[PDB]
Length: 63
Length: 62
Image (tube, rainbow over all chains, first blue to last red; front, side):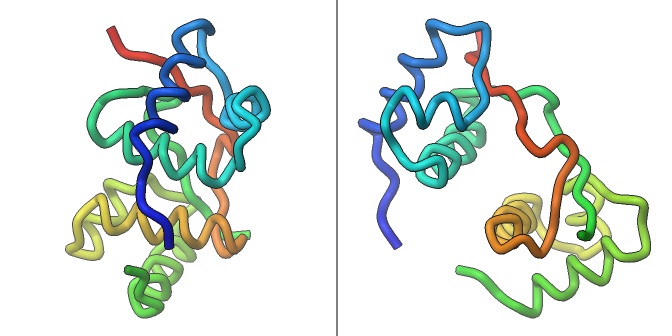
């Protein structure tokens, strides 16, 4: 595993600031980053209340 | 740190429901929400679980 990067966090935040909101795929596309790393950073940031998401809580289920 | 036992407990719980939010899963399993979410997203990567909606919209708080 690789550690969390505050630089990536800040890049994500800068991107989101310019939008009404964005899905992780678009964030990753703009940043030229992996969607997985972007998501990984988004979750952690959400824990610190640095980002939010709609809806707040998804419903999980089985395939 | 991912436990397959925790994964299986989550799956067993989700099986009996139409679906559930992480808070309810955590409370039912007697676990913390953070751990449950960790396992849920890890399993999501592997396609062992899914969520509605699949792609949330992220934004900044004010």
